[PDB]
Image (cartoon, each protein chain N blue to C red):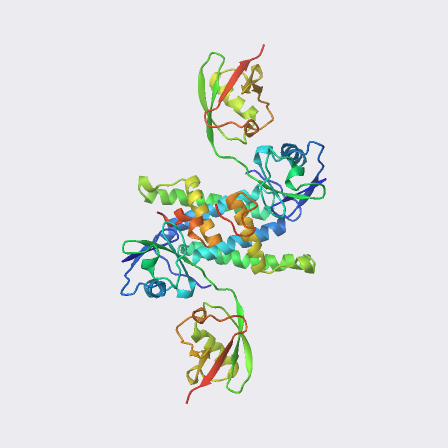
Length: 96
Length: 96
Length: 151
Length: 151
C-alpha cells in the first residue's frame, strides 16, 4: 500500500519483467514443485500476458514488436540483475 | 492445458518459490519500472502469501515454521537455480 | 544406494550397479520418475558442482549414502531438422526435442504421403523408436534423419 | 554531463562539477528522481563494475559522455531501534530505513506524550532531519537515538 510513481515506459517494462516471471513459473513447474492452485496462477498469467503482448504490439511500430519468447529473454536478464543486485548479471536488462 | 503432477510438499515449495517471486516484484518496483496494475499484482500476492504462510505454519511442526522474510531467501535461491538452470547458482555467490 | 534431491527438497533413492556411471544414474532416474536423460542436470550435494559424464561417480566423491541434486530442464524450444525420403529428397520439419518419434513420424507421414507403419526413421546409423523423445538422439538444427521403407 | 541508466532503460542526465565525487553524483540523483542515496547502487556501463566512493569518478572509468547504471536497493526490511527520552528511559520502536525522521518522531511523540515540534532527535552526536530517511544515518538494530527538548 505504498505506491511508487512511474512514467510511460513502465508498461513495456512490466510486460517483459512479467514474461520473465512466467518463464520461472514454467521452469519451476518442471521440477514437479508447483502445486495445483500454483499451476492455475501459471496458466492464468500466461493468458493475460499473451493478450497484453498482443495489445501492446499493435500500438508499437514494426521494429519494436516482440513475441512472448523474445520478451522472456529480456525479463530473465532483468530478474538476474535484481536477484544478484548486479548489472553484470544482467547488462542487457538496461537496454544497451 | 497439461498438468504436471506434484506430490506432497509441492505446497511448501510453491509458497517459497512464490515468496521469491514477490521479492522480485518488490525489487523491480524500486526501479520505477512496475506499472500501476503491476504494483496491484505485487500487493495482491503479498496479502495472499501472508495468509497462506500463516495457514501452512499451523499444520507444520516448530522446526520447519518459516516467516515471509526467511521464505523469501529460499525462493530467491530457487529462482537463481532456475534462471541459470544450475544448482550451483544461488549457493554461495557465483556468476554467468 | 544414492539419494537424488530435487529443487523443492523432496528426495528419492537410486541403487547403482558396478559401472557407477553418470549415464547409468540418469537411466535409473528416467525409470523412477520419467524425466528423460537429456533433460537431467545433476550436481553433487551440497557443493552444487556439476557431475562430469566421462568420470565414474566413485571418482567424483559420490559413494553410498551420498546425495545428488537434480534440476529438470524441459528443452522444449523449437528447432528445424531434415528428413530424407527414400527417393533422396530432403524436406524440412519444425520440431521440439520433447516431441516423440511417433509425432515426428506423423509429420513425415503427412508430407511424404506414406502411412507411418510402412516406414521407420534412422539417425547416425541407429533406429529412432516411436515412444522415445527426439531429445534422446541428440538432434541438432538441420541434422538429417533418413526414412526407410518397410515391406 | 553523465547519463544515468536504470533497469528497463529509463535514462536521464546528471551534470557534475567541479569535483566529480560518487557522493556528489548520488546527491544529484536524489534531487533529480527522489531515490535516497543509501539506496543507490551505481556501476560503470557496460562493464558493470561497482563505483567506489572514496575514488573520484575521473579516476575510475568515468568522464563526460559516459553512462552509469543505477539499481535501487530498497533496504526496507523492518528493524528495531531505541529512542531515549530526556529522563534516561529507552523505549523500542519498530522502523524501516526508508521511513522519514518525521515519521519516527510521530512514533516518539505518541509514546512519550511530547509534541513533535518540542523536541529533536540525535544519533552519534549529529541531528536527525525531519525530511531525510532513517537510512541516511546508518541506524542498526538497537542503535540508540537520543531525544533532546526544545525551549
